[PDB]
Image (cartoon, rainbow over all chains, first blue to last red):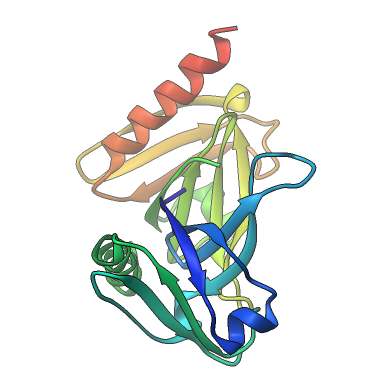
Length: 107
Length: 105
């Protein structure tokens, strides 16, 4: 389904609105980034939030984190989402290849 | 559900009938291939057609494409589905494993 990274949410209004707190799995997929958590019942990983690439305003990273700005149409509502992690470059790389691959009509 | 590949529909009687045209994601799952299109409003991939492995006559690949024949029992109907892709092999491999694990019980 796509690469997964264990990340920790650092406070922003959007993450606050979505009641995000603590650590999650961010998964880079073909047309979206998904945020996942252990299901309370299922006790396996399940989606908590979707961010279709075509609905993100911008995204970036550094040696300490990964961050992006969801646009109005994203399910979380508009705003910045930032996650602490030392694999910022890796998530950025995968998001970037998904998008180019996707923009190339995908095939 | 499994690994996904971007694919382009190749004109075929069945794909015409199902109305397929353009790019899609072919997802090879534990018991079927699922053809997903990107959501109009949502901008999220969404199931379009599903082909359970036990309902496929055969399938295969080429450096230029991947293809399979659905049996009469598929929701899409019987016929050939071909998708131009340069990953026909990785897909094919994936289906093998999918199917290998299935009857591996």
